[PDB]
Amino acid sequence: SDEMPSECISRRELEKGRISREEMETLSVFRSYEPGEPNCRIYVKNLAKHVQEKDLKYIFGRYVDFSSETQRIMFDIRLMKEGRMKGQAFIGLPNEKAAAKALKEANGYVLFGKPMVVQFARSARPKQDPKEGKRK
């Protein structure tokens, strides 16, 4: 592989920017939004103006084994840079377990001072759900 930089976020750094349900059902940024549902895709609100989709790779690509093509092939990020939906993002992950983990760890993350609102993907129109890449 020769794609993305050879550093992604450590759990001890990610865990500094995180909330419980006890703050979540208190925060105005969480007023209608809840984690933990089964989906291989996740999406985020309240990203910084200070950031691009090419930077969100640093955290969200932590859950993708980049030495294996079958993982990173199913991974990509777009950030909504402007309009009435500015500072929103979509991320497909290689597994619904990787999304379950990443929702438990990324949710509340204080990127550029701003607490990111990490959720299961709200709607998308594929034909079929994915599977495990190694021998399934």
Image: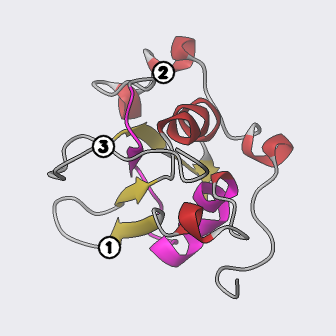
Front residue (pair 102, 2) = 2
Figure check: 118 above or below 88: above
Per the image, the residue denoted by label 1 is 81
| Residue 82 visible in rendering | yes
Q: Name the amino acid type tagged 3.
A: Asp
Front residue (pair 75, 105) = 75
Front residue (pair 127, 11) = 127
Q: Is residue 108 magenta-colored?
A: no
Figure check: 99 above or below 20: below
Figure check: 16 above or below 3: above
Front residue (pair 55, 4) = 4
| Nearer the camera: disc 3 or disc 1 | 3
CB of mark 3 within 8 Å of CB of mark 2? no
Q: Left or right of 37: which side holds 2?
A: right
| Nearer the camera: disc 3 or disc 2 | 3
Q: Could you classify mark 2 by the number of other residues whose Cα lies within 10 Å: few (under 14), some (14-19), or many (20 or more)?
A: some
Q: Name the amino acid type tagged 2.
A: Met
C-alpha distance separating marks 3 and 1 = 28 Å
Per the image, the residue denoted by label 2 is 24
The segment highlighted magenta reads 38-62
Classify mark 1: helix, strand or loop. loop
Q: Is residue 54 magenta-colored?
A: yes
Q: Name the amino acid type tagged 1.
A: Lys
